Figure 1 (tube, rainbow, N blue to C red):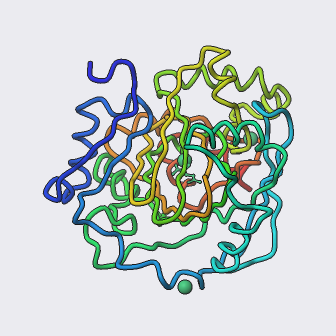
Figure 2: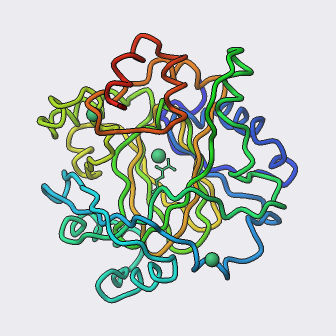
Length: 331
Ligand SMILES: O=C(O)CNC(=O)C(=O)O
Ligand SMILES: [Mg+2]
Ligand code: NI
Ligand SMILES: [Zn+2]
């Protein structure tokens, strides 16, 4: 078995190897990359996502989210308070202000220390889940707006034709902006490209150990756990690396820098934070190996997690028994 310790692998494809997305994903998994739940892909030195980022300030962040934390430094929830719309220009200016900017620090490790020590005492503002793309339409390789769609994958593998579309989302982050512990909708893959700015640190639990994370989360967030059998789908819970180590949860960590891709694999729980002003683009995707994960994925039926138009059809076809009660939570 490849990668038995489930370490995060880092790939350096050639421009030749970067031409066929599906085949490179299949390659990574032949080397055991999926066992970690997360891989990094450094694009060939000749590749670019677009020529410059000079004109992005006019993107609108229609609903910035102020991420308000409750709990203790290593175990907290966050609630997203909706703020007034602002442009990316305005946001970047806000991220760079004295109140919100990245503090002085020695290196990534010192900054990680400061994040976990001090996160709860500040409420950074996140521009998340904005439909759109920053890839140039002439970028042909690893263009997150030109991937084959999950609906087409399900059609090719399973023969069923469904409604729905699959498009990317932009995330504008600042220091301390946080993504809580989650897997993807329907335990899909994700791919994330860091277009510009400061890094993003990731924590990940190997898919084969995901249930151990869930068991800890039920113990750490006991009221949430009673309210919904899949409350991690709410994307509100944070657990520090220190806490994970204390409870023997297997995990890994890695820092993504501008110009790099990350791929999360089915049922790879991940969480993380932003080091400073940045912009990432991400999208979900599927492969043939995903299908069984999609069949077994948990669902939020309490009605908090409230998920896309396209997810309906995945639940309808892959989880027909759930379909009934799940759409009660989604209606
Ligand atoms: O970048 C972020 O804020 C969150 N991204 C993801 O969870 C992902 O790409 O799967
Ligand atoms: Mg613009
Ligand atoms: Ni994710
Ligand atoms: Zn729920």
